[PDB]
Amino acid sequence: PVQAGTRTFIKELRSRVFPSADEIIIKMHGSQLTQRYLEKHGFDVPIMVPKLDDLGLRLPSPTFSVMDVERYVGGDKVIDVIDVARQADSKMTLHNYVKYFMNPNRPKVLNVISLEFSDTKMSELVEVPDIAKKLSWVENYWPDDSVFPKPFVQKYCLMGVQDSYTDFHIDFGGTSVWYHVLWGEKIFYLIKPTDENLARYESWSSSVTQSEVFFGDKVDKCYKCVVKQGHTLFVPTGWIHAVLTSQDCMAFGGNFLHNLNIGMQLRCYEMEKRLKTPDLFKFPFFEAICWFVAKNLLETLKELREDGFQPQTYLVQGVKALHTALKLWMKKELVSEHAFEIPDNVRPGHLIKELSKVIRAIEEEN
Ligand SMILES: [Fe+2]
Ligand SMILES: [Fe+2]
Image 1 (tube, rainbow, N blue to C red):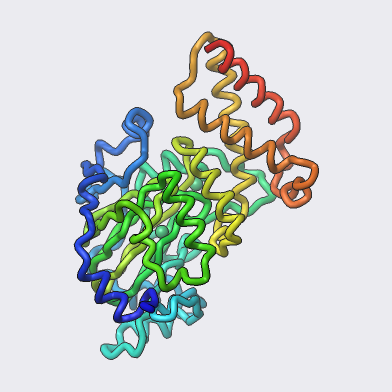
Image 2 (image 1 turned 180 degrees about the vertical axis):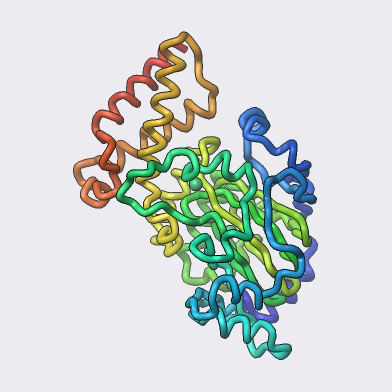
């Protein structure tokens, strides 16, 4: 059996000529990627922006090194590191990872993919893509007076050695991600979240043979997307993907929830709860933000209704899925595990009623 992450596994991966991600992604200039464009054409496939012009994305020059990351972050910080050949999570001091990274002879393939630095001096060196900030639920609906700590999942520093490999997964909470390669190269294996593919992914995730079964073989198409230096890739809600560091690489990326695919975001959240995924620990208050969002979406629909307008389809679909999720979390036999995420400022039972009728109305008056 070929174990994910091992040298043998990588020889196969590097030799297969998968369908090109050019068959499904949309390439565009940074100025075309607007909230407006996304609301009209949707955000259903990955978007590639080869040049960073007009993205609003700011970051160190191409010579920024891992040594520099250690300076701005602090070698003492303990970080998650993946022992790729064993597909296991380990720990290290940022200091030793950098020592391991610069050592010409690496006894093992180690990868760093969860280093969030918005709480460090390196944060001032990075401004995330404007589009992420425009769409971000956290940027738009997180109150300045919540008891819940604000989630910081917007700035990650990724460093991996050649052949680092991250197996197929869906970003935590169904978030979308922006990913930029500073230097080196990353190759993404993308899989569309069709109802068939999600189902199989959840089955594959809960099978003991997960590490010996290439998930790419269980679906009709697994798209290969090469992300080269200077390029920026945006992956939308629910997309299943694996990543191969084809060569020593440093990249930056971030996660964000938004209003375009709420249903899918909710679906991914529930799946994660069924699989008991450790990633959910990164967006601990997913439910709290959903409550905050339901208040804002309620307001918009109320404003539109009271003035004779019909909301856009995706907004009605999204609110409907939100309504269903909120009602579920409030069920008598389940509310005890959900109550702590209900914001002080919201009235659960009432917010659900208002939502239920605004929806019903739109359903009848249509
Ligand atoms: Fe990912
Ligand atoms: Fe967000």
